[PDB]
Image (cartoon, coloured by chain):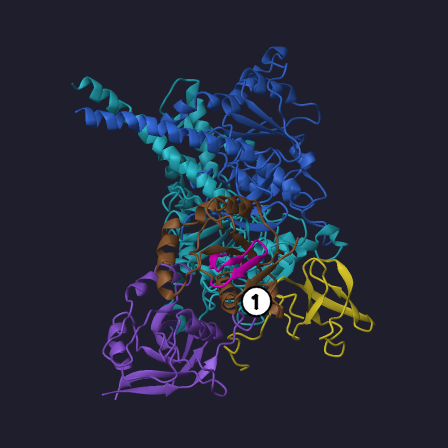
Chain colours: A brown, B blue, C purple, D cyan, E yellow
Amino acid sequence: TKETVYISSIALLKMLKHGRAGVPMEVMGLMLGEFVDDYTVNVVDVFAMPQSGTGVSVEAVDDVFQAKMMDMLKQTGRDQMVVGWYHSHPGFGCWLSSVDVNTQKSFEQLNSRAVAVVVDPIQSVKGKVVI
Amino acid sequence: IRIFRSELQRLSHENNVMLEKIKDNKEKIKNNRQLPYLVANVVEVVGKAAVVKTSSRQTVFLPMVGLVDPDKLKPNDLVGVNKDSYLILDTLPSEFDSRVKAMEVDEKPTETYSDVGGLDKQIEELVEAIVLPMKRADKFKDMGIRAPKGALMYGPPGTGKTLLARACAAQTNATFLKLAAPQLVQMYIGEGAKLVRDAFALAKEKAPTIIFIDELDAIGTKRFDSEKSGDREVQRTMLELLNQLDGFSSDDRVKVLAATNRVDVLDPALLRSGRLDRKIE
Amino acid sequence: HEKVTIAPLVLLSALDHYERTQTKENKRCVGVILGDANSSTIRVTNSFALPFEEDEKNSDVWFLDHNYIENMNEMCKKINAKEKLIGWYHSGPKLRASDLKINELFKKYTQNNPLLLIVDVKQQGVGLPTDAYVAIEQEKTFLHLPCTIEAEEAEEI
Amino acid sequence: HRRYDDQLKQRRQNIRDLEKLYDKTENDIKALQSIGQLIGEVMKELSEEKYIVKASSGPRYIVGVRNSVDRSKLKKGVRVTLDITTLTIMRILPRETDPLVYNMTSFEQGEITFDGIGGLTEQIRELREVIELPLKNPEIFQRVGIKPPKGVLLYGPPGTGKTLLAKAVAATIGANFIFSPASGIVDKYIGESARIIREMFAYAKEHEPCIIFMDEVDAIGGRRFSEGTSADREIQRTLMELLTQMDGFDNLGQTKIIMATNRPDTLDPALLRPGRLDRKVEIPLPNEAGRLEIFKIHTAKVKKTGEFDFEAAVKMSDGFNGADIRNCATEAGFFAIRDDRDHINPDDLMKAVRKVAEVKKLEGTIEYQKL
Amino acid sequence: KRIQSVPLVIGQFLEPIDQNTGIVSSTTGMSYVVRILSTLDRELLKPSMSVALHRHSNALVDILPPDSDSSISVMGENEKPDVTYA
């Protein structure tokens, strides 16, 4: 089925900038916001995760660096928890790989409402972002 | 005292736990290794990196793989590569390229020296060429001389000494390589040259080998007194015998016995103290 | 003279922090800019925020977080290694007399002349009210430079 | 007290062996995460961040770049690394065109030196004049005005030590040298024989002190215009390759061409004329004065008696060469084996010297190209 | 026009057939007949002009400028005037 996922105007500009790190190198970063029941995913703020040579794998996530940055974001006015993360798949369509399934499954015990977003900055040059 | 011995005792236990993870990773590697892979040509071996080229003429870059070492790797080498990830999972299987067209896999023939008679005059001369250096070469270095790199084999317009050529590959019980001269000329340019070029490449793997050439009159000429084109319809293969025998090959146990029909028509450049020493009628 | 270019990513980042930090009663939100000032055209490709609290009747009381300066080094440097601190920005329409003392705190981290960026959050002006100033030796004066909009695939899309 | 401690120290040898196997296994899993990466040369430039790189298979795809590479080295002609999926420029690699260890690296092992080529001293200074002189002091040719000789021709009958002239230089100077067999470059698929020659000169512009050796090549200098061509299509272009690199505007003078052949009449007369091969080095048969030092070269490492005379074999030699004396020294060893003699007697030498003069049938007097 | 973006194939124009339709020959050796993009024009190209194509569909993308890279000469003279005619 379908639902409505709201994304703030500031979050779209940051995801397109994060995907500019490189075309062959896939990028991944966290997000912030709230939810309304199960039918609404609100994307307010996004986080930029550091790069990893494993190509966005389950072992490429650092919880130590995550806990240190989210504690500093509380002083900046962010009261919202992590709503998910975005993963760029440049050059291809919108689909999930075998690595993304095992990676997203590891976060099911942490936050079951997490969202895995697939953004394609290469095909977004037409004026409408394919995501 | 017991504390120092307890840490070393638990060290072997922690190594066994991590060893099970290594054994599980090896099982994943064996599961990731399935017979249908492809073979590519190694281009170049800052960091550690290896460049290869597939047989389809596709150049793919790959990082250094733990399955291979820079000592074993070397440019211009055929190793197995992955079809999807294009990673080398297999090293060189102890063979440079291949036997190409044909190769002689026979071990020993049924012909010996007991089937001939009255030939002892010329038999002792053939023993001093391709036979004794297979054994007494250690004694040859003490005298300061060098083993002959070949001997011209000819005779009257007839059968010839080929009956004794089998006895040389029999009583000595060494490696024999049969190379036919008329089989070295083909319509494809360069394929006939790779036959002799790869003949000495595999001759370096097995040292006690003897290369035999039948009917040397098949390939040779100075190629003149004609009209324009038609050159190198012969000498393309002859240049292999010129460069290889005078090149890195023909060291100690690498020898070539060239049998032919008549000495009237041949290339005088083929006879040299660096290739064919003994010329025996 | 030199040139200053502010990307719309930095613009919307500074303008959104007004309601995010609950800024009211004519206050300011002090941020930070990230760009390359080595060339003749200053281009800011990244920006963040810093907590700022100042009394209305007391101009000698202001709060600034210097620990967050070291926190972005563990993040941005692992993504874009060319990002450095060229200065900071303010969300107030007009600068105050406290900006002279702010330059003393960031002069150690910045490797060049800090850039003073002013972004109007009221949007009551025409065109591009966002202005930039460069603090040099006069005692000290602020040299104004024209502000443009960054044109790149990471923004116009 | 030390009984249990010595047993734990002996087990440390197996522990250190397992520690070396842990890093090898962990690097295997990390290596499988990486995929293949295409390699291609930059063709042209459309935009700043948008370029065109020709794939190694022959199609041309428009590819992108990243922000982690320098745009100055991304210009045309530079070989870069592409991606098998996104098709973008990733890594910049130095220029290497078909590296071949057999056709480039000489695998140098010192064997023959100037002391073994002796007797050619009159003709040895001809090689050092076009090799040692221009490389050591190039300023001499500039003030005089003469141009440094590019190509060098080596002719004459075989067995005169012509092949040893190329090996004596590799064991002395030590610069980058290239072994180029004639029938090894004739490989034919589609236009292959013509592209191999251009692969050799790619290293000439990289390493300036380089010399291209040619060992017994009568092939690529052929003539063969039209009888119907007998499917020479790639060979005729290979003949023209020597008529381009040594002719056109490409930089020369830092790379010497040493060419060796048996009969120059078979080669294309246009290739022998000046402008390509500047110097023709005559390598005649060593005379009685030239051979006198050659007998001592082949017999230097050969054990013999105390009384020896090499002047006897000088008159016994009729139209021989420098190599045929090695045959005389080889046959002299087998003559002493039947008599159980470790040292070769002078009587066994004269028997082996004439043994070459008994065989004959080598011709050797039919070469009229001496000039 | 911007849907194509990075993954492009180098084509070559051959002959016009129909309005906003033309035959193209890429470097892969397989000639295809596709439709001309609306932002392009038949008068803005040449019979020998080289164009761009899609990776899979191989549809016409953009008209390259009249500069052919290929090999050999490429751009033009480099350090040629080293001598005179005398």
- State the extent of the magenta-drawn residues as a range: A24-45
Location of residue B88 with respect to C44 vertically, above or below = above
**Image quarter for residue B280?**
top right
SS category of the residue bearing label 1: strand
* Identity, as a three-letter code, of the amino acid under mark 1: Tyr
Residue depicted at 67% across the width and 37% down the height: B184
Q: Position of residue D98 (x, y in %)?
A: 54, 51
Rendered location of residue C20, percent (x, y)? 42, 69
Extreme residue toward the top, this view: B114
Left of B274 or right of it: where is B16?
Answer: left
Residue D183, image x and y in percent? 60, 46
Q: Is residue E65 above or below residue E24?
A: below
Residue found at x 65% / y 33% = B216
The quarter of the picture where residue B117 lies is: top right
Check if residue A29 falls in the magenta segment: yes
Which is nearer the eye, E23 or C93?
A: C93
- Residue D67 lies in magenta, yes or no? no
Mark 1 closeness class: few <14, some 14–19, many ≥20 residues within 10 Å: many
User: Label 1, on which residue?
Assistant: D51
Q: Nearer the viewer, residue B195 or A126?
A: A126
Q: Quadrant of the N terminus of chain E?
A: bottom right
Image vertical order of residue A58 relative to residue A119, above or below: above
Q: Is residue B184 visible?
A: yes
